[PDB]
Amino acid sequence: QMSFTFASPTQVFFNSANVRQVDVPTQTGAFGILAAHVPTLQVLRPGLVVVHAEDGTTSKYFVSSGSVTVNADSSVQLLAEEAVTLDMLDLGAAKANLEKAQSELLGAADEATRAEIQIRIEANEALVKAL
Amino acid sequence: VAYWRQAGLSYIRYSQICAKAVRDALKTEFKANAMKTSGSTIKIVKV
Amino acid sequence: ATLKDITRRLKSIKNIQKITKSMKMVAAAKYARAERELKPARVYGVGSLALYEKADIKTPELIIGVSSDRGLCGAIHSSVAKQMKSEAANLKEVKIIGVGDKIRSILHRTHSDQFLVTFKEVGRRPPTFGDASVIALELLNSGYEFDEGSIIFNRFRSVISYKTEEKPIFSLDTISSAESMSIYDDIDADVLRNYQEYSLANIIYYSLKESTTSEQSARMTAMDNASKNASEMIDKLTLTFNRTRQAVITKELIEIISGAAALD
Amino acid sequence: TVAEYFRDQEGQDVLLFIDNIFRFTQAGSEVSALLGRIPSAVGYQPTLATDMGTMQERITTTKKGSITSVQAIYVPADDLTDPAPATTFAHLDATTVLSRAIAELGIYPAVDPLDSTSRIMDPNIVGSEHYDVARGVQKILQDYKSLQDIIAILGMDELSEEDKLTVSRARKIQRFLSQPFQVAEVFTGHLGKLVPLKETIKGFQQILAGEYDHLPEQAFYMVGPIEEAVAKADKLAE
Amino acid sequence: YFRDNGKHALIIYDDLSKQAVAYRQMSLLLRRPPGREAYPGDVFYLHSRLLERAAKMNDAFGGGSLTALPVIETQAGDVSAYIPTNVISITDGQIFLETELFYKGIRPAINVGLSVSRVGSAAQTRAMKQVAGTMKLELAQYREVAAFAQFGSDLDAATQQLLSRGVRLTELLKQGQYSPMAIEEQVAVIYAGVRGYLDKLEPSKITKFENAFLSHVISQHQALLGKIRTDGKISEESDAKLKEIVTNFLAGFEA
């Protein structure tokens, strides 16, 4: 178990809930942080957060940012800046937004805009993976 | 983080764009609610 | 005094009584909102600091007070304010922020310059996360990074008491590089910082809320207070009234009773 | 004079509506001037006291009957400090302040309850059963009132539900004071119901005791007898 | 005389204030006492009888009536004022008029709560009663919040509306200078507000609506107005006729 604190200002989803795993877009890739994992600190990255709750379930999520914090212990706290359930997130929009995003990228100014766009693109994808 | 950290872009900057991008995203019913937690009564002074 | 005077007074007091009372619910509502807002949030801020703790740190190298731009609510802000700029001598580099402005009082008279920022519209439409990030981000850009900040806000205890707080601002990414952080078997002064960063908002939001929640809840309280006073007075004046009235009535009734008649 | 007939002669409890003493006093006073009489402070006829007094003294319980005097009272200057009502108070021993508001709550009858008062409520005369239950009630009503203040502004589970319970009990009690109406049955439908005291004392006590609390409140609404409330309670629990 | 000639006459006694003074004076000059508050006692009686001589008579008197609208023009809300206190015990209600509204430009003036018809409704058109019943209330609740945190402070939405509504109704409750109405016009506009149709409008435009709306129904829906006068009352149809007229017309009024 890991008392997985899965949060956003939006929501605390798992609130130190004895979860088996959360699959987390850290910045390079991810990892499916398994039930009590070593300390390591990772800052997220948008992806989907998939909270393989210990239970059998996995609940699905999209995450945009924050840090998940993998304590030594059982407390894992994903504090995703933005942590959302996919429910609230529109694939259609994502796509369209992506349409746009991709459109925008082309005139995106500098790595920072591009980045942004991209963040957004990546994001849009990153909802889109699941979504 | 090279696609944002490149030069600059805070984890916030990043994040916020991510998050912003969430704000950008979202389904509808749901979609109202976003800006609520945003920089809104954001009115930054140093005063 | 002459009935006018009384009224004049009264008038206002009643007004007050309303106004305050008005402000009381108004605040209470805000407050109520804020109250709501605390749930994930609670966690969220609690979370935010939740790790400079297990894996721990201390400097040997941004002060900031995070509360309101509010008074009539009470002297909350002054509370943090106090307890903020009161310190500052020890620290290092001196870079202070008062977000909140009635806090910027006990600080605002020694600098105007070693402030970095202030938030305005503190509360109002209840202050939030975004903002916390918003305010978080640029903030980073600054030359004092853990000349250990403190974040001073009124951490609520109750809708009426909060305790004017400080927490310390781990902007170490340094000594936090050193130590039992290795254990965070990998982590990078990126991702580190990029959590430090991230937590700056988290907290920021939070502190902001702690204070502002406190304040708003305090505003009800202040607004109560006022009305207790009011309530009495209002009562009393009403006497003062009768009297001046009667005093009057009577007096004339005198004049009337040949105090101007038979006996002109 | 008429009532003296009914009291003494007819051995009765005459009900004497005098509406309003304010107008009476005033009427005397109008003459005072003209009579060249010195009136008084606040302008009153000098005789205000005697005027009231003898008259009040002429009302009583003889040992033939009672002239129970129910005096509709327009309130001079909407205070009582206006000497007469203060005096009136000397002769008042059951006081009725009607709550326009409660009535407005659709409550029928719907007095100011806490100012539906009597100096003559007693654990003695009306006995403690009455008294105490009432004291509990009056208090309770207030208590409920107290909680009303909180909750009102703060939404709910601003209470613990014993407070809620009492609140509710109070509501039932509140409602039990509502009584369907006979005279205005023409409007209301139902009828003016009459409540023997024990059912009353008992009644509220029971509600208070929560013995009934597991039933709705409109039950009590438009009821005379505590049974008629109980019956309606059941009925509202369909 | 009219009353006995059936006739329902309206007397406006304008003002007893003036009388009172004179009369009081008269007593005094007669050396005779005045009375309470230094002014005559049975000047009440004067009036009491005077105004009792106004009545709504039965049928025998040709339904006889004199509707009396006595007038007092107040100094400093002196109602406390002897005669006013007196009078207060006498009338069938009093019409409190409030200046603030006047300066505000608001005409009517009124403070309503202070205004009273003890009588209330029994002489009222059902038409109006039906739309008005609802209005009185809309204001009533509105009024508490009419008072509450009036300034630039939020409210809960319910109340943001009631306030809006209330405010609208206020405009509606204005009535132009030398611009009498008729019950249908009134009911019409009341209907308009009640059925919420102009909360829509931000307040300034209400007045414009009303006129326009009026001149409009005046063109067409005299059909209705005439009707409403006829039925004295709104039928569900008349309502329905209203409903469109206003909504659409309103739509036209706006856009």
Image: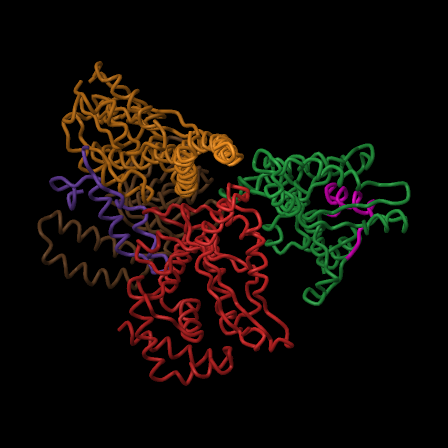
Chain colours: A brown, B purple, C orange, D green, E red
**Residue drawn 29% across the image and 20% down it:** C82
Residue B45 visible at all: yes
- Residue E211, quarter of picture: bottom left
Is residue C38 visible in this depiction of the protein? no
Q: Is residue D208 magenta?
A: yes
Up-down relation of residue D192 to residue C90 (above or below): below
Quadrant of the snapshot with the C terminus of chain D:
bottom right
Relative horizontal placement of residue D9, taking residue E6 as reference (left or right) = right
Place of residue C214 in the rendered image (x, y in percent of width and height, measured from the top left): 39, 32
Give the left or right position of residue E166, taking residue C110 as reference: right
Image spot of residue A124 (x, y percent)? 25, 56
Q: Using the image as rendered, state which of residue A9 and residue E85 is in the foreground.
A: E85
> E57 left or right of D52?
left
Q: Residue furthest top?
A: C90
Q: Is residue D223 above or below residue E190?
A: above
Question: Looking at the picture, how far across and down is residue C230, in whole percent?
Answer: 45, 32
Please report the residue visible at 73 percent of the width from the left and 45 percent of the height from the top.
Answer: D207
Residue C137 magenta: no
Q: Which residues are magenta?
A: D193-212
Horizontal side, residue C172 vs residue D50: left or right: left
Magenta stretch mostly in which secondary structure?
Answer: helix
- Rendered residue at 84%/44% (across/down): D66
Q: Residue B30 at what x, y percent from top left?
A: 36, 57
